[PDB]
Length: 251
Image (cartoon, rainbow, N blue to C red; front, side):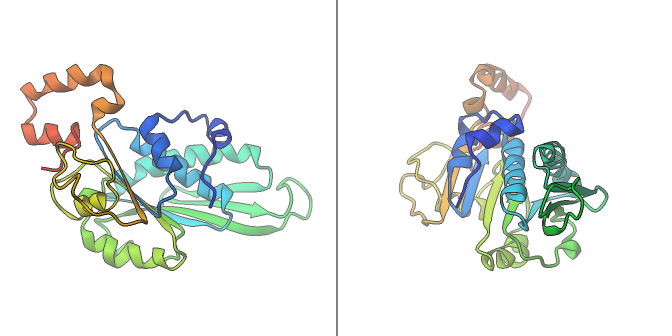
């Protein structure tokens, strides 16, 4: 049900831009964001995780990226936010295992500093890596974040993530700069209701699934004052790399 509110953002120190805000307001179980670099993907994803850990005690979630080093980015941001925020929820206590990328938020039946405090629930967030399929062994997930999803093999989604989500009817936030016409393109299109758009083949004539909602932004959509700087980089950046990483185009 509940999405993080303006009050929750204010507690966090978070001031979302327009694309971020659209993602947070979406209630879709499959949110797919095709965004250029510097889009605010990481921060937005991290706020989603923070909200679940406190607002749904006992919730479990993963952030998955192509590598552990990539996964550490969103994980690290969730850790900072959770450790700080916990201060204003006296009935919580945070436990961190940095090496195992495991974050626990223990929920109690009274303030943690009170005598007799009993643990009632534990929310859990882990960082996972697509290049380490061996550590992708089950959990019952309420939510999942896929970072740089277009670089993650579809099998990771279809075999190791989607099944453990459909159980608790959990949600997925699937984020990436595009890597051509692969599974991330397909999932994007399933949620795309913004009509015909250059860079997106079959936009405007595509069908959509009701559980899907998709978002699109070039770097210069988020940062208009950087548009000229982005364009002038084409002098030394190959065209395809430019169109994908900044244009967020499916080529």
